[PDB]
Length: 489
Ligand SMILES: COc1cccc(-c2nnc3n(Cc4ccccc4Cl)c(=O)c4ccccc4n23)c1O
Image 1 (spheres, protein in one colour):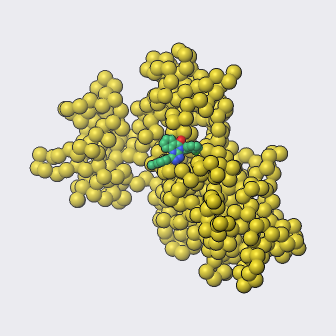
Image 2 (cartoon, helix red, strand yellow):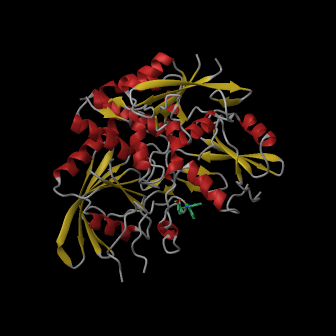
Image 3 (cartoon, helix red, strand yellow):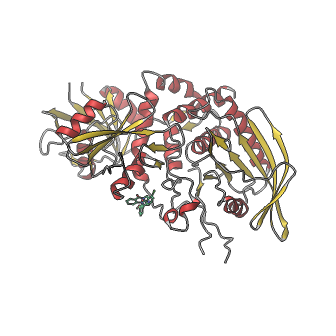
């Protein structure tokens, strides 16, 4: 669960909640009111509340006095498990008890103000057996609207003295507690119909041709913020093991110690110099053309990077960062100078030719294994150089033109392995490019008359690598990129 996340509270409201309803070690996370885009970790320690800043410009969640994380749920899981790791004056702050939110806003099934006719319309067009939703009455009360078979049933939810009930039995502290209770224990109608709450009603799948319509509606005060926070709440489902990236020998192979690859999707390296030679902070991304999502090379991982590219038969690399951003190294130069030949362990690379375009540089690389001439293949490195240091480009035209070229290159190469995509941590810009590429590929094959579901695509990608698509800004950029691609069709 992710109930410690309160989406609509102020700092003073946060302070009051921890002072009146919490104890020492009680905490909550919330979006920052003083700096929208940021987050605040509010912790009760010695009868007092501390407000700690969490930053995200698009690469990772950066906790002040803490570490860099892929998701807020990964951050909370780590600190609830590892005490002594979080400091203010250098004093330790412990996350012991999550203070739960009762707010139903970011639940997939909450529709707020919605008619009984409209709820019936939606459950008929998009609903299947067991599809449900929770909307407001119609006053101060709520309505649960289920589909079965086929019919639609309306169950009235009473709100009596800040608790919720279906007209008898238990009284719940939140609509979420009620929904979970009747999801587990389904209500039986007198004539024996089981009102099974199987899955929430889909509210995000749109027909591609109607992108402009939904973008216009999501731009209204914002709807994009609401849609994104509903996706963020689903991240609690994605805390898969990242045990390999934790091994003593693998520690220094990570750019960010706590941003790790899922064990089930990580790229396992097989070249193996005959002890622990099978690790790279990289994951295979499969839609539903594959990708490898990875971090910017470290001086000690360059050789491993080339072993991965060789093993996977990848012929295209998408670099989405400058080597150095804001005076900080984001990726080491893992390729030779133009016309030069370098050996990276057992792997040999020649930089045949570089071509400078407006937003990017193309490098034609020749990769082979040392002592085996019949292993040579061309690797095309597309280096996007103009992405802003913070946030996203103000227009998607540059990214789209670039992705078009990457796609046509990859498509011209017979039996080419997955496309390699990296930035610094390999989750934000990497996640964004991969998702846009996946969505635009659906529109390539099936045309403007196709269903696209942006947060479902992101969720699918996030189960293969942690925190793929970091910010609400990148989320809005994925919509704008797809809108512009459809407009030029
Ligand atoms: C079924 O699911 C799982 C099964 C087994 C292991 C994991 C697992 N893998 N990484 C972590 N980290 C992340 C972690 C740990 C050490 C150093 C850096 C990091 Cl970034 C935790 O902090 C953690 C805390 C509590 C429970 C599991 C955790 N976990 C998992 O998720």
